[PDB]
């Protein structure tokens, strides 16, 4: 019942492509601006698509990219709401990067934590939370996306022993916060995957990014606790971030970059 006929879709502009397929901006039923994520032929059977797509179908929150429709015959299409500004990663590195300061950045983080707070209540796990999988819309709206490893964003337990939980998502969120505060820089500068895994097992943590208030770096560090259960909830992360400039940094002053 999420199913629609293919010719309901006008694929117009190519937006990019990944290991699993492409993403197009498009038009639905001649009237509705949409995004379509195309899956490469041979990635998944129709019966196998039903089993995995249950999650994206049950999740409906204002801070997750909304699924609109599905074409579950090869090649499989996933039709979702259209986010005008692309990925948070591109946004942070682009021309807008320059002008973003802490208040905008923390507000973006709060929207994201809210999205994940919803996933948390629903008892799901994201598994691939990072700036590249957040989409930006008008008015600096950010929404979590993408439900199809990248070790630098992955919690130790999950990278090593496949222990993926909401708490491993929390760890990735902490890494996302360094992306937000460095304007999109790859975490652990200079370190390759193995060096990262070794160091993180030995207790290494990224330091406070320049101009970033120690209080926010504390939050990152809490997200990075060795012990998954010590890690804060997204409910906490969301409330902390929404309230940040009153409750936590009431005397914040603008700087050159943050």
Image (cartoon, rainbow, N blue to C red):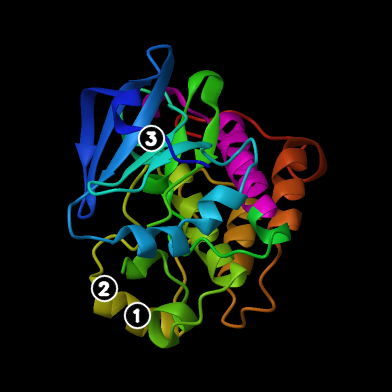
Q: Quadrant of residue 88?
A: top left
In this view, 117 is above or below 249? below
Residue 92 marker: 3
Image side of residue 149 versus residue 227, left or right: left
Residue 34 marker: none
Q: Which residue is mark 1?
A: 197
Q: Please say whether residue 112 is one of the residues in the magenta stretch.
A: yes
Q: Secondary structure at mark 2?
A: helix
Q: What is the distance, in whole Å, between disc 2 and disc 1 at their CAs?
A: 6 Å
Image side of residue 222 versus residue 90, left or right: right
Q: Secondary structure at mark 3?
A: helix
Q: What is the distance, in whole Å, between disc 1 and disc 3 at their CAs?
A: 26 Å
Q: Which residue is mark 2?
A: 193
Q: Quadrant of residue 46?
A: bottom left
Query: Most extreme residue toward the right, as rendered?
Result: 247
Dominant SS type (magenta) = helix
10 Å neighbourhood of mark 3: few (<14), some, or many (≥20)?
A: many
Q: Nearer the viewer, residue 258 or 133?
A: 133
Q: Are marks 2 and 1 in contact (CB under 8 Å)?
A: yes
Point out the stretch of residues depicted in magenta.
97-118
Q: Residue at x 46, y 45 (%)?
A: 145
Q: Residue at x 62, y 52 (%)?
A: 116
Q: What is the distance, in whole Å, between disc 2 and disc 3 at their CAs?
A: 23 Å
């Amino acid at each position: 019942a999420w199913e629609i006929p293919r010719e309901s879709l006008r694929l117009e502009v190519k937006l990019g492509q990944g290991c699993f397929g492409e993403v197009w901006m498009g038009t639905w039923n001649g009237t509705t601006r949409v995004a379509i994520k195309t899956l490469k032929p041979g990635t998944m059977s129709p019966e196998a698509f039903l089993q995995e797509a249950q999650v994206m179908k049950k999740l409906r929150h204002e801070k997750l990219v909304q699924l609109y429709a599905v074409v579950s015959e090869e090649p499989i299409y996933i039709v979702t709401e259209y986010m005008s500004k692309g990925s948070l990663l591109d946004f942070l590195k682009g021309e807008m990067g320059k002008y973003l300061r802490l208040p905008q950045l923390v507000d973006m983080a709060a929207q994201i934590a809210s999205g994940m707070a919803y996933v948390e209540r629903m008892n799901y796990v994201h598994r691939d939370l990072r700036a590249a999988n957040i989409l930006v819309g008008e008015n600096l709206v950010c929404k979590v996306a993408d439900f199809g490893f990248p070790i630098k964003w992955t919690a130790p337990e999950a990278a090593l022993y496949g222990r993926f939980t909401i708490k491993s998502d929390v760890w990735s969120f902490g890494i996302l916060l360094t992306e937000l505060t460095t304007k999109g820089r790859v975490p652990y500068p200079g370190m390759v995957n193995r060096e990262v895994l070794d160091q993180v097992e030995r207790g290494y943590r990224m330091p406070c990014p320049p101009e970033c208030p120690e209080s926010l770096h504390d939050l990152m560090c809490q997200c990075w606790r060795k012990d998954p259960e010590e890690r804060p909830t997204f409910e906490y992360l969301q409330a902390f971030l929404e309230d940040y400039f009153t409750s936590t940094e009431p005397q914040y002053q603008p700087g050159e970059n943050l």
